Image: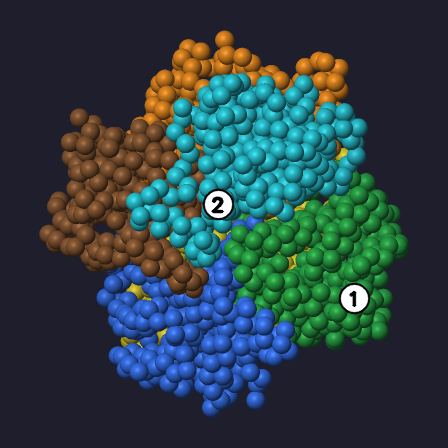
Chain colours: A cyan, B brown, C orange, D yellow, E blue, F green
Amino acid sequence: FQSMDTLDFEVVNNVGWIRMNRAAKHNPFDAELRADLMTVLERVRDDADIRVLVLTSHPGSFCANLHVLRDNLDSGPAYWQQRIKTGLRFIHDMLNLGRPVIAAVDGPAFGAGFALSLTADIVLASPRARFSMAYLRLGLVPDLGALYLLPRAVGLQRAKELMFSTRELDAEEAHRLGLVMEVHESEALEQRAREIAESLVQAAPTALALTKAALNVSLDSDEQTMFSLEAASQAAAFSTKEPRAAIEALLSKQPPPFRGFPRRS
Amino acid sequence: FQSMDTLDFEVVNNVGWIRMNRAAKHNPFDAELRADLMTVLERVRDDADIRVLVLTSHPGSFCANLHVLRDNLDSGPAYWQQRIKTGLRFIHDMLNLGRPVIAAVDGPAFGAGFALSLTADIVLASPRARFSMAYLRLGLVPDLGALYLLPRAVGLQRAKELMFSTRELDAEEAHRLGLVMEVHESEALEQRAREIAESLVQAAPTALALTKAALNVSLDSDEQTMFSLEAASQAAAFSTKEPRAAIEALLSKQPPPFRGFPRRS
Amino acid sequence: FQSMDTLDFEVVNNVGWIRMNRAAKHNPFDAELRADLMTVLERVRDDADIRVLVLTSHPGSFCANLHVLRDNLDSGPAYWQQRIKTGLRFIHDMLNLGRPVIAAVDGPAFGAGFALSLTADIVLASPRARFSMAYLRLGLVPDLGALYLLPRAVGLQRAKELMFSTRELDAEEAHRLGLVMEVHESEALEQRAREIAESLVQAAPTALALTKAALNVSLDSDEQTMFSLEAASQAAAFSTKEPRAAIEALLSKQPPPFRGFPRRS
Amino acid sequence: FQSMDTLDFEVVNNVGWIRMNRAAKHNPFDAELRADLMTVLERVRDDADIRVLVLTSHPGSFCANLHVLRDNLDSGPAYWQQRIKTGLRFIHDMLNLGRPVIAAVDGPAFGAGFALSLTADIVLASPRARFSMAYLRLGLVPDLGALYLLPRAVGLQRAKELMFSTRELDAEEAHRLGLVMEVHESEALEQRAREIAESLVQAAPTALALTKAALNVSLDSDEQTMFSLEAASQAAAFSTKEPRAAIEALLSKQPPPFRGFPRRS
Amino acid sequence: FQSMDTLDFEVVNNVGWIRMNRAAKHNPFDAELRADLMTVLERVRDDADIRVLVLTSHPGSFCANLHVLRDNLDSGPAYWQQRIKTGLRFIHDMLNLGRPVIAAVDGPAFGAGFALSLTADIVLASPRARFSMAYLRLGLVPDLGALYLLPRAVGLQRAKELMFSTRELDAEEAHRLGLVMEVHESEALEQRAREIAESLVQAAPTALALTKAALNVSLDSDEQTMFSLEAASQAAAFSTKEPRAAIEALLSKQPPPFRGFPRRS
Amino acid sequence: FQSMDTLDFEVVNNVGWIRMNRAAKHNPFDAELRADLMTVLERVRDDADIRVLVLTSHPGSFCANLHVLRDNLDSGPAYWQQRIKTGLRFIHDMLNLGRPVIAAVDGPAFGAGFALSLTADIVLASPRARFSMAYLRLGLVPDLGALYLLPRAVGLQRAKELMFSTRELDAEEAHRLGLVMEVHESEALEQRAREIAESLVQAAPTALALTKAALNVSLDSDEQTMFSLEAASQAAAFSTKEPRAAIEALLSKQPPPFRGFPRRS
């Protein structure tokens, strides 16, 4: 249990809970939050027993810094090319994280917050969740990998309308579009994230990491490359203890350690 | 009309009907089914008069072998890398088949069965159809090209939730997501597959094969490559008899040989 | 204000209105329309003050030439490979146009017309709009980049069913599938296109063009390439006047010049 | 035979000779040359009897406009993004030209001239030929598709050293690196280009165009996509008269119409 | 030891020797050779103890069927699209073979023979070896994956000159271009192939197969995809016995089982 | 001037000199060297005045840890998948570094050292330089991005022979293959690296960084994507001071600040 400037981090039942802790400020994606998230990721890397992550906030907020923009308006192309790279190093790290990441969204996920939610493996939301890409309001292009991530979630035409309109997607529509897996009342959201995360603790870390890594590049790739990635990944999976444990159980007419997510209740 | 160990194959009105014939066992995707399907594909290749294929089962099943997994748990990486390749040779062959393939799903399409349904050009289902990727329950990564095929059907976020949750998609949701083209009552399903397949018999084999081949790689490719594929494909299509027959008919105020699928009734 | 053989072009409030003007003939995509559209694009390129384009028709039509096909049925592969390239030069130009293009569809968008609508950034439609790829009825493969564009809008399985069935998508389903952003009554359609287009006049031309160019290739590309494109694009955006104007306004508790699209009314 | 402001164009024995005609100015790649080259390309498109092109200059020059750069130094990102696109439209057209293009280089091919030579199918050079990418001397990135074309010719490491060093490659090294097919004395260069071009007149236009189009995208693509392009292209080639003529000749123990390039003499 | 119609197959010291046995006919790549090679590949798949393959011929020939072309000149696009696919199934199988393939070339490798040599992992040649792509002499595009394979070996410009010129590459130039690893006198060629093949018997089958599979797709892919393939492949390699055996040996100041190829002598 | 455990770092005339300082141990690529190199990269990022980097060693060595391998032989797939990712984070950072990196190689560059040299923009070597990929000797696949980097430098066939043979490339051959830009006597090597690095100090940081970023992804990409990257990059370059300074100088008949590398002497 560690309380940081921009988040609280707690490991309970092999689940790393990242609770962003500046709800009134809407947890802005600034250098301070980036640094705290990097600290979390480094702790996660060094500890295989942190099996699953939940990314969330105090209720009513998620993630949604103009002074730092103002101060750097004329800093020049070389500066901005590098500053974008700093942001992208973080997104790169999220996509490469070999643990499942569940985002629980109970407030605005705008700009950086929407990009952040797009790096999660599973997104759960309440009816309070709002998603928006509003960079064009600032005369800017979408950053933090949004140009890459959004079309892979919703297709080209939908990405275009979202980024040009800068409109807010509500939870129901985000669910309709497959950005959000399930919608729950605000008062029930954390428990659902808990149930799902704790179920994934029982899943094989190797199978999890390899499945995530392959899915994350699938739409960048081609048939033979993905077929070769499948072959290497399955070979790796079969050299772990989990398939035997699962197979023996099922042949003994018993349920395997990972049975999927718990039924909604 | 040939009755095999795992399927019955019948050609009627230029349509090859593949009826998997082990409903009680849920038509497991094993070496025996693979070999029988390969036999069918080889017969299809040698006979241009088998214009369309329907892949189906005795009602109540579709396609859904743990002993062979158990026996090979510690066979090693080299073995598994090769065994995955054997499976992938088959999927490669399905995707490369120059005839339209209609899958008619009236039962569970799980794991290999879901991958199999993903290789079809058109999927028809009843309310009994269930789709699931449950490899993670075994501590394994999805195989038979699922990592490649699923995101191309539903996008990255949806593929992720399906593969991590291992949940069952019902027919209605599969239709909503575009996996399934139409949902029909079990008692009406075969006749619809018949109507659709027999309509495609009238379509140009060259246009059909080239359209399928281009679509199958579209999302792996890029603008100039696909533009070049379009140019080569259309040049090839114009060197067949079908455009003349279709054009002459339409200019004579008559319907062309292929008018689309029959209206639902 | 210029009246051409196949369209009328009018610039009003920095919006270029392209009104195809052969409604009775359904504005066929022929050499004449291509040439007139090319003239428009060349005028747009030379005039940065034409900030947004609306592509539309006299009401009841959109875009939906068999004699030229008949006359060239046996012209040969070299001929057809080149003629396809001529068509594709135009589509290439549409996708590369650095201004937002709004299509307002109040009638059939068939074949070439559907391809044309797919090159727009935003599609608005009435309940009269119908979309269809019916090339297979002619024994031909889809042209004008449809094999490339359609799967990027709707995924592989949906593209396949649309192109094999040759069915007509109504406005409601096209909206459901994300081809169409909003559906409006025919009598209200033009005003909505007007409202949206005039709002985009306030958006930064640089941010607009760079966002469009990046989105248009996102699904052809990969993580590191798109990350590098993001970095270069943002560096370019920050060297324009619009971010300062937007940021100063927002820090002064005032709305920025571009606030998104006007609320539906 | 047409004499233009920046080139002379002559068709002799089905070969289109493009002779750039401002040797003292080193045939700068300006709006005037672009427009004249576009005129040539349009004439080539409309006339299938112009089977092969030779791109060359009065001896001692090839292709190697700072005032237009100076005048536009502060024109801004939107302007430059569009002006680059104008240049790239031309390069796109060169790469898409379905006729073989032979470049005969007897002088500096610098910047735009090097890019131009990279779009040719065959490059012949004299010992006077020099190749250089010197954009970095101007504080600029390489343009006219050089970032795309050069690594496909020489690999990444070599492209990097060339573009960072801005060094001049002589004919011998360019030949060593495969940029240049053959090196001939200045006094012999045109006749070799003539011999090679006239030999290609005998080659099948369809096979030529399809081979060029496939090669031009090969390194952008993947196994299954290129295999599908091969299949469509060969199907198209077999629907022409040339294979029969070639096969009949060879079975009659006679040489085919196209036997390759004439022996060096 | 099995003597077939088009080749003799012999396994000696864990090396599968494929000796094509129709030298006078230049071992034409016909249905008969394809079928015999497929038989070999199937035997190789079923026997992990066949660790390395050598593909060769009786001396003076390698691999270089016009009647079957003549008979099918007007068979049509659908036919040819399928026949090309049959050929490509074979090439696909060669590239996917998880054993190292050494080609020993002591004669013409023309057309199909050049494509065949391009699928090998290592090519050894004598001064008698000649390589040529001469499809354009027949009015055809290069087949058997040449459009894909050649640019990956030599770059775009070189592939173009080779395919347009249809010239013969001698051993020395092929070695210069990296097609050929080593050139040996005809009388010494087989022994060198023997030495190299028997050395690879000591290499880890898993590392071999995974390295080959990754290299074969590297130029089709991108940074993050290849990084993910590396991670999965190394994880798989570390679950084999060979690293321990190699590491223990080297730490004991002893040579590992695989030390590279024997010195030339 | 900072002396670290595995390297000394010195900034002289805007050039960051990285001098690896464990020559007797051959500067092994271990956690300690990685951490020190990361420290350097972080200092480079924070200081735009460190314009160019030289990566080198005390003479006689470059970069060429079995105990850490031995200790982790059976740590499992999940562990190794993550440890490979740690290594790849570093390589990713090298490729993304917006400053030119010159490697000066005066000794063995083996395994990790060869991968490291492949991330440099320019490689200079002495006749003492040796390059080798010898992972297969350990029963392992090449790591640190070698599977990605090597084919982009030398093509597929050459990468294969290098990785399967595990042979040592001498300086002369590495230069022949374009891995090495220039070969200099050991006693002259550092001064050449100095001359080249100090010349690049005069080059535009924006043009440098954008050119590097585009080249690094060129072979992963496609025509339209690279054309769009070119457009965005040039727009960014024109918003810097360097083009004006260079253009004004050249129009004044004076040399620009960056004239290329100094002549060899």
Residue F177 vertical position relative to residue B51 in the rendered view, above or below: below
Percent of width and height locating residue E204: 49, 70
Residue D23 vertical position relative to residue B205 in the rendered view, above or below: below
Residue E174 in sight from this viewpoint: no
Q: Please give the residue where the numbered disc 1 appears in the rendered image.
A: F22
**Residue occupying the point 57% across, 34% down:** A12
Question: Looking at the rendered structure, which numbered label has been put on residue A208?
Answer: 2
Determine crowd level at label 2: few under 14, some 14-19, many 20+ residues with C-alpha closer than 10 A. many
Residue extending farthest top: C265
| Label 2 to label 1: alpha-carbon separation | 40 Å
**Amino acid found under the numbered disc labelled 1:** Arg
> Quick check: E182 left or right of D112?
left
**Residue occupying the point 25% across, 63% down:** E72
**Label 2's element?**
helix
Residue B2 vertical position relative to residue C265 in the rendered view, above or below: below
Percent of width and height locating residue F72: 59, 60
Percent of width and height locating residue C168: 31, 28
**Amino acid found under the numbered disc labelled 2:** Leu
Determine crowd level at label 1: few under 14, some 14-19, many 20+ residues with C-alpha closer than 10 A. some
Residue extending farthest left: B1
**Residue occupying the point 24% across, 42% down:** B62
> Quick check: C150 left or right of E31?
right
Tell me which corner region of the image, top left, top right, bottom left or bottom right, holds residue A133: top right
**Label 1's element?**
loop
Q: Quadrant of the N terminus of chain F?
A: bottom right
Percent of width and height locating residue F223: 55, 48
Subunit that carries the residue with mark 1: F
Same chain assignment for discs 2 and 1 = no
> In terms of depth relative to the viewer, which is nearer, F116 or A253?
A253
Q: Quadrant of the C terminus of chain F?
A: bottom right
Tell me which corner region of the image, top left, top right, bottom left or bottom right, holds residue C27: top left
> Quick check: F241 left or right of D93?
right
